[PDB]
Image (cartoon, rainbow, N blue to C red; front, side):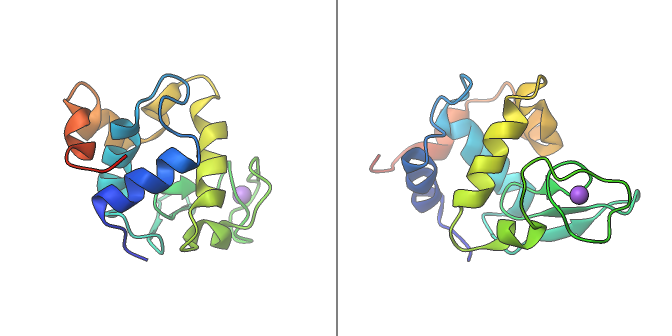
Length: 129
Ligand code: NA
């Protein structure tokens, strides 16, 4: 599913991301925009053989099992295909583990390069939250 901007904000807010680990909702929306363009089914392959999955582009080396990533961990205890659902719950739950792990939202290179230090409140302006 391809979310609208305010639709995804609302969904993220109901799953408890606003201000999670001190990261306001506009941070998450901004990171989803550039990681995937709001498209749950998104995937992208990395040089090291891993793949990034879903709205938040979560990586199979550490966080999910795809069966084709050697030696990798599955710290979220889920198959990577669960991250492609129209129901973003599974991705949100996994992202809460990522952002708590020590580097905060710097785990998302699109966030670091395109959202960090910007007026990320823009991303939820206009929305009925
Ligand atoms: Na894995």
